Amino acid sequence: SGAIYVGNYRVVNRHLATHNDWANLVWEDSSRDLLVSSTTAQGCDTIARCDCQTGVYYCSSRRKHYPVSFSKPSLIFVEASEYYPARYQSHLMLAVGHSEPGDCGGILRCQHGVVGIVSTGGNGLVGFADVRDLLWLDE
Ligand SMILES: NC(=O)[C@H]1CCCN(C(=O)Cc2cccc3c2CCC3)C1
Ligand SMILES: [Zn+2]
Image (tube, rainbow, N blue to C red; front, top):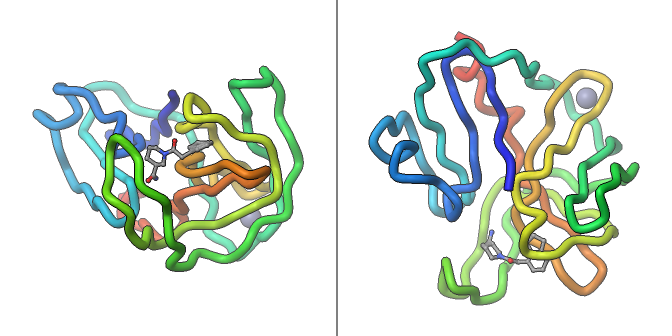
């Protein structure tokens, strides 16, 4: 579990979005596993606007943060699950690292700010849904 709070927006994994997220829907993209809802309070997270390929992510299944090198946002095949049929998920970045299903929503950060959130994993890999291209989150 986990979310990003920036301005009047809340960014969560689309498969974990609540009834309130869907009732206050701003934008969602099944292919990115992302959903943005509107909030009443002002969020304080800063979004990175860069092309960093190193950062640190939060791993709930270990209660630890880990440094990682990660790939650039790309189309990657994601195995079948209880939330989606087998498909290509876009704007996804992979890293070698520990991850378990309940790890979705853990934030990835670089020196510039929030890069993305955990969205896929397994076999000693971890995948992050990128948010750096969503320039509207800041206006
Ligand atoms: N984006 C998707 O299609 C996901 C939808 C929810 C289900 N999902 C996974 O649980 C994949 C997975 C396996 C093993 C470790 C981990 C994960 C996610 C977090 C770390 C994939
Ligand atoms: Zn950066």
